[PDB]
Image: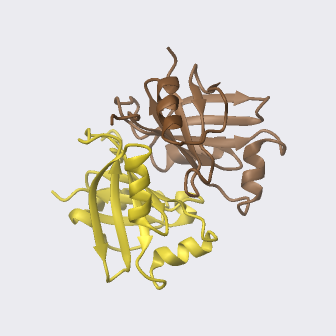
Chain colours: A brown, B yellow
Amino acid sequence: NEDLFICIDHVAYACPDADEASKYYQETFGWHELHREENPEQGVVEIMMAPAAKLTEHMTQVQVMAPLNDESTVAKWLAKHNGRAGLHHMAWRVDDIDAVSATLRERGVQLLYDEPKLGTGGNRINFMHPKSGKGVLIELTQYPK
Amino acid sequence: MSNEDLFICIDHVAYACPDADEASKYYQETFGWHELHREENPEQGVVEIMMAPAAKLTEHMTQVQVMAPLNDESTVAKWLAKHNGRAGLHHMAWRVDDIDAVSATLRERGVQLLYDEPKLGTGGNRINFMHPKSGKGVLIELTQYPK
């Protein structure tokens, strides 16, 4: 036994317009926008929001995701969900995605990628099958280095 | 009178599954998440389990709240049905220091709350929710620790 997770890294929220949601989060909730990224290839725009201007070690953030094209994964997810914004998935932070992927694998855990893939920042990520998540899609994510 | 953060952190993410014990077994067995509290309320027909990634919680550490129907008349059973028997993220709860004040502020900005007055939650927390149209596609909970 041992802890394979530091904390929930972020909760991904999918919506048709990331800008609109971020401005709502800021204007209405007073949340803080910490980072914005656009990935033409994935056809996804992502924005990181937090309840404070400065993150604390285990502070979980909210990730706003919106499509850049109707071919993107996010667009088809939104289509299959009343085209309405909704919680998309949970990402849990790991100190060593390889090491932890070994442990998870050893415990019969099924991942999505054979190998971790690069994501936001230099993050090395991977997921879990929506079934392996009892209905919920769960992402594994390790900060760079 | 500079505006101050209304939220401390995301208190917990609610996951609605048909079997809490089951889901809880999974988080501990497989994922190795620690179970910190289990509660059962007949009134509402719900069973809840608080899971954390560590044994001890850090000030701003978010937990996963496993919800599960105790019968088919529970609000949670319906939801599960609504989401086609598919378990899944149910809601997000944000911790606040003073729910009455945060609620008053939120209303001035046009937010709609489910209850006019805070309800009593688990552990003595005072809670309320921000109408889906307010949370924007998501049901957001406000949670104040009893103090």
Relative to A98, is B54 above or below? below
The answer to whether B83 appears left or right of B28 in the picture is right
Q: Give whichever of A3, B87 is nearer the camera.
A: A3
Image quadrant where residue B117 sits: bottom left
Quick check: can you spot residue B106? no
From the image, which quarter does the N terminus of chain B lie in?
top left
Relative to B6, is B69 above or below? below
Quick check: can you spot residue B116? yes
Q: Give whichever of B108, B8 is nearer the camera.
A: B8
In the orientation shown, which residue stands out farthest toward the left? B147
Residue at 70% in and 29% down? A38
The answer to whether A72 appears left or right of B144 in the picture is right
Residue at 84% in and 43% down? A71
Residue A93, position as x, y percentages in the image = 46, 33
From the image, which quarter does the C terminus of chain B lie in?
bottom left
Residue at 37% in and 56% down? B105
